[PDB]
Image 1 (cartoon, rainbow, N blue to C red):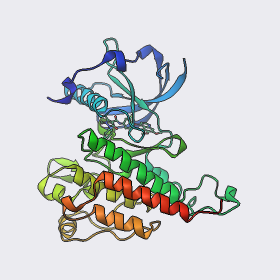
Image 2 (cartoon, rainbow, N blue to C red; image 1 turned 30 degrees about the horizontal axis):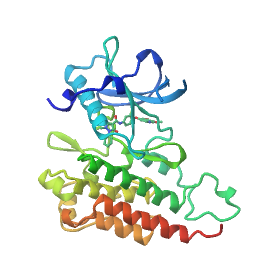
Image 3 (cartoon, rainbow, N blue to C red; image 1 turned 90 degrees about the vertical axis):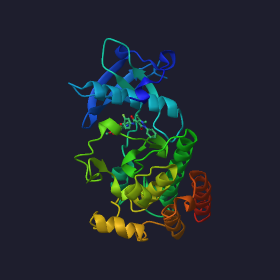
Length: 308
Ligand SMILES: COc1cc2nccc(Oc3ccc(NC(=O)c4c(C)n(C)n(-c5ccccc5)c4=O)cc3F)c2cc1OC
């Protein structure tokens, strides 16, 4: 009933299906799927891409939902720190297909968890002992990038609504990208999504006003960003460790209960998390302010690493 019906620029976005060779499925959702593919001449060069399309026997409403996803991607536009649309297959002859840039390291949560034994706060010479290690610089840099992607999203007058580390993808050269799997995520088989009424909701990432009043704003996205920071500086742990996500949890959150400092945080990063978790939405920092602050922390962190 909405976004799928926005105008489409075929001369800009249309990619020939014949120039696309589909390979292995990457991820399987409730309605749609993401498939690894080789594409030729998308940017006379071959490139690995991610192709979102619908599963066999998709309904009309599922078709509408994928088209709505495509139009939202187009509206948002290009930024380094957002998963970028490379093209689309919308013409008669074959299925609706959305082609985005391939991020080879996958989601940030799983990736960070794989590096628990490959993290040092700062490398020490000889640095080859810490080859491919994560450092404080990496984590602050990831945080900084997501804040810039979220500032960009805000400037498009968009609200994410599902900001989390599972929705951050890691590309080449330590470049992180904000995304949403949407139709290609199975939220009914995902423990991050909790049943509250008719819907499955990411309760551990949701601001109190969102939980109680159903209010989604850019300011509740900032709350979510604070939970993401906690995920980054726990190296991909799950929020509110061991805590039952019930009525008591929601009550205590409204009353001012917050998560403790995660294992790999700096004092400055933890205060930033707490700032993002202000009970008053108006009192949370903006994403512009988060970009500024995290830029300052990235800079301060560099002064702690001066060997070279
Ligand atoms: C190696 O492992 C993988 C690499 C992968 N690499 C790239 C892509 C992959 O899957 C996808 C993930 C996300 C999306 N995103 C969309 O379709 C998006 C839409 C419609 N909007 C509106 N947004 C958006 C953008 C900004 C802010 C709010 C939402 C979207 O991100 C598309 C995908 F194909 C991968 C899956 C992998 O395994 C599962």
